[PDB]
Amino acid sequence: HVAFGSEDIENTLAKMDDGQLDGLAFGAIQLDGDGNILQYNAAEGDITGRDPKQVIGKNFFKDVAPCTDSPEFYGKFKEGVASGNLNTMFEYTFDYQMTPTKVKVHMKKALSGDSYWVFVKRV
Ligand SMILES: *C(=O)/C=C/c1ccc(O)cc1
């Protein structure tokens, strides 16, 4: 088990494969520094209606999730990528190619130093 917002969430998830990530209680997306989707779990697809198997490789901010292209989400992502001190939490509404859905979001640098987690749960 691992809870949304856990202080060491990035440690726990670093040890996980696809199946384990698919079993999480919350949506989990891993992005590279450019916002390309590296991983996308089953729980996230349950929130958004995206097929996880097919969004891999797409750009989260340009193509998949344009409603997050804003200072409030994408702006915070780029600030944290640039600082090396991505770890930030906030509320948001997802409303592109889905019923508007209120969520809470947590972004955090992965240990694969290279990538960046985006965590989502319904509120
Ligand atoms: C806004 O358009 C948000 C879209 C979105 C958020 C999260 C996802 O996993 C997929 C699309």
Image (tube, rainbow, N blue to C red):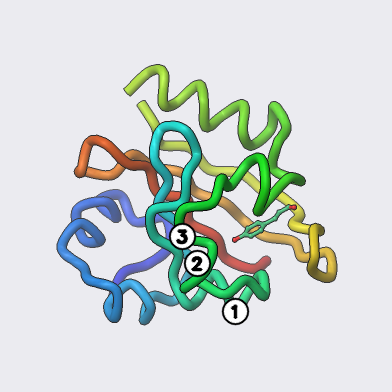
Label 3 CB sits under 8 Å from any ligand 1 atom: no
| Residue contact between numbered discs 1 and 3, judged by CB atoms under 8 Å | no
Nearer-the-camera pick, 119 or 89: 119
Which three-letter amino acid code belongs to the residue tagged 2?
A: Gly
Mark 3: few, some, or many residues within 10 Å (few <14, many ≥20)?
some
Label 1 CB sits under 8 Å from any ligand 1 atom: no
The residue depicted at 68 percent of the width and 66 percent of the height is 123
Q: Position of residue 35 (x, y in %)?
A: 50, 39
Q: Which residue is mark 1?
A: 46
Quadrant placement of the N terminus: bottom left
First along the sequence among labels 2 and 3? 2
| Residue contact between numbered discs 1 and 2, judged by CB atoms under 8 Å | yes
The residue depicted at 33 percent of the width and 72 percent of the height is 21
**Any mark on residue 106, and which?**
none
| Residue contact between numbered discs 2 and 3, judged by CB atoms under 8 Å | no
Mark 2: few, some, or many residues within 10 Å (few <14, many ≥20)?
many
**Any mark on residue 56, and which?**
3
Nearer-the-camera pick, 93 or 38: 38
The residue depicted at 38 percent of the width and 18 percent of the height is 83
Q: Which residue is mark 2?
A: 27
Which three-letter amino acid code belongs to the residue tagged 1?
A: Asp
Q: How far is the residue under mark 1 from the one under mark 3?
A: 16 Å
Q: Is residue 73 left or right of residue 41?
A: right
Label 2 CB sits under 8 Å from any ligand 1 atom: yes
First along the sequence among labels 1 and 3? 1
Which three-letter amino acid code belongs to the residue tagged 3?
A: Ile
Q: How many marks?
A: 3
